[PDB]
Image (cartoon, rainbow, N blue to C red):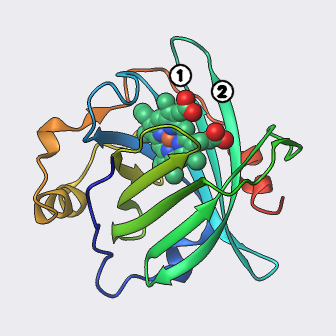
Amino acid sequence: ACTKNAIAQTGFNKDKYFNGDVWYVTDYLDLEPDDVPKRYCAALAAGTASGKLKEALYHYDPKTQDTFYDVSELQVESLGKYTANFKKVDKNGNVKVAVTAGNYYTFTVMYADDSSALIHTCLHKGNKAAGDLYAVLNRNKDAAAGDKVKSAVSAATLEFSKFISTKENNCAYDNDSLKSLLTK
Ligand code: HEM
């Protein structure tokens, strides 16, 4: 299902990435066909909350209106490479689906700077078939991918021309919920 051992950025700066702020997905590449929709909105917050490494996720399908949030405790495999549980929550952190063995994702930061990043994730959810998902992130939801992150896509032996943009979906995000979910 997933096939890639993504390599984390050399010299990854964890405190800068996990600073409590929001990252927007601007472009994505799924290696498995028919795995995710062709139009999508996603964002996350990443930070340490009371000593615990956390991510809060948001997904929105702009055609179906399917919406869900997750809160994730990350465990460290190596610098920039994590295994995350997930619990599905409402935007206020109330649990809808508890943490469960077999529901996890891996998360590898392949490149990051203050404004942009390239990540890989492999999602394992119960019975479902997994597939490699790469995402270009930016701190600014409207930013076109710049040369640092596009060069990193090339250095991963990927073609940025294959990535699908999220920019034409009228995506609107609740940054406040993502930040507050880090504590939940
Ligand atoms: C930003 C990095 C991402 C991470 C870490 C991530 C992680 C996850 C997790 C944990 C779930 C399961 C949530 C739950 O059931 O509670 C999920 C579901 C899903 N994600 Fe992502 N995701 C990311 C980005 C994306 C992107 C960019 C897309 C496609 C444009 C996408 C498409 C989906 C879809 C379609 C599901 C629903 C799968 C199902 O039917 O259960 N995700 N994702």
Q: Residue 35: horizontal and vertical position, in percent?
A: 37, 30
| Mark carried by residue 168 | none
| Mark carried by residue 67 | 2
**Given contact means CB atoms under 8 Å apart, are the residues at marks 1 and 2 in contact?**
yes
SS assignment at label 1: loop
Q: Is mark 1 within 8 Å of ligand 1?
A: yes
Q: Amino acid at mark 1?
A: Asp
Q: Amino acid at mark 2?
A: Thr
SS assignment at label 2: strand
For image coordinates 51% across by 49% down, the residue present is 124
| Mark carried by residue 61 | 1
Give whichever of discs 1 and 2 has the lower sequence position: 1
Mark 1 surroundings: few (<14), some (14-19) or many (≥20) residues within 10 A: some
Q: Residue 27: horizontal and vertical position, in percent?
A: 33, 40
For image coordinates 32% across by 24% down, the residue present is 34
Q: Residue 60: horizontal and vertical position, in percent?
A: 57, 28
